[PDB]
Length: 213
Length: 213
Length: 213
Ligand SMILES: [Co+2]
Ligand SMILES: [Co+2]
Ligand SMILES: [Co+2]
Ligand SMILES: [Co+2]
Ligand SMILES: [Co+2]
Ligand SMILES: [Co+2]
Image (cartoon, rainbow over all chains, first blue to last red; front, side, top):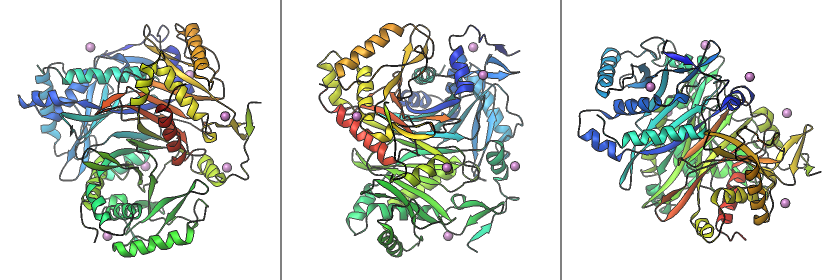
């Protein structure tokens, strides 16, 4: 199987986990701006498009940290070996969105082939989940390309035990000499602390400042 | 009657609506900065005050999009022909707020007459709802003039089926050559997507950049 | 006793309180940037560290306003004479956090002695609440020093009657000639309005712009 049961008994977060899961269930959202000045340059020297690269980079970062790939399966806590991005797609024609996923791959060119393929096949499918059930080993990525925002937060009526992170991007902006992308991260406190989210963001930024291949 | 029953059966958002209403009930808030550099100029060339104009402009924008004027009435989904602003008023003397509403009008001078009239009559009424029951065809507007903010979010214990948008303004600020007003929009996902909110904001900005009359 | 029963009967917020407590239970979070340019200078001319001073300053501000020190005790509404800060501590070694508190004092040097003492004694205690039960007369302060954010919000599954404010700080940043610290304030609407939060923030800023002793 593609996940491994986690050793809660010996975890340094064991008390945190029970506290934030059942005693005081909560989570948080944070919005920060990622500098994509370097990445804009890289993309310019290539044929990649922005959105597919950001999915790639975000999935890559998530796949490096266990605490972003936890879930409850059969009442037990597991870590997925790896997770695939579930991203939103906007249909111009109906002005509605759909959520799709494709397999992640550490090889950026194979990821692009996966993405183009999924898009080829469901570009005109206006169902909300054209592919049917969402694979359990997922992360959620959404984009609001039409507007910049300083904050985004999802108010959810019930989030018991849903630990996959939700990342939302807005339209980027030029702030002085920099091109900044607002990114909102929303997690559950049972599995993730402020530290973990900050480590994800610092890692993402690093990725944005590095060669693609 | 002043509303029309909506055709859910043939709506391109029909699956979205059921999903976000009953399967995974949620909403979101977003905060963005509206450039009010042009509007400050217009106001300077006139006798209008800032707050009443922002209510006006926001109500005007809301009244152009159906998805911001939905509600459940008798278990059915309706669109109001038009909605009136319900705005907050601060009382200096008690340091408490009240919520008022007046009829919207596409004629800015009649709107001002409505506003001055409502204010005349309830300026000193410290009840929370001096007028009694809030008309069902409303939008909510609030202002935090004493402080600038980058984000605002309302955490609500229960929001089942309340689809009127909540807009909150902070104190504006000079950012370089621009005067920016932080505005927070909070909607329910059953009726509104990221697209819709972004379209409201882009429309509001346009309005701010145009002649008043 | 260290609290006083509040006169709800004659309060100008009496209707607000019942409304926001039981009819439409809610709260809000707001994130604003505090200019700590002056304070950086003061700290430079001294031996104080940043975090302990911010706890100090925030607790000082809270202790000046009643509406930030309310609670329900025995079904009644009370105001604490004073509240102590409950702050988070990060352990590098385990990469987990703990929450501690020490007695507040209006004398900054005695506060520092209290803080160093509590830290001395529990620096290596990785329990979530090394001291055991949190004193009821508390405010919550947390810090995310590793990342800057524009917004922070806690999504809480149940907040019935918890009125202590939650303040969260991010990493500060240089914005032009200024050093700004993002601060998020999260309150319950039964006890606090936008006015109150804005008054807390304006007061905090004032404090940051003043001599320490
Ligand atoms: Co339990
Ligand atoms: Co791996
Ligand atoms: Co249903
Ligand atoms: Co019309
Ligand atoms: Co009651
Ligand atoms: Co006192």
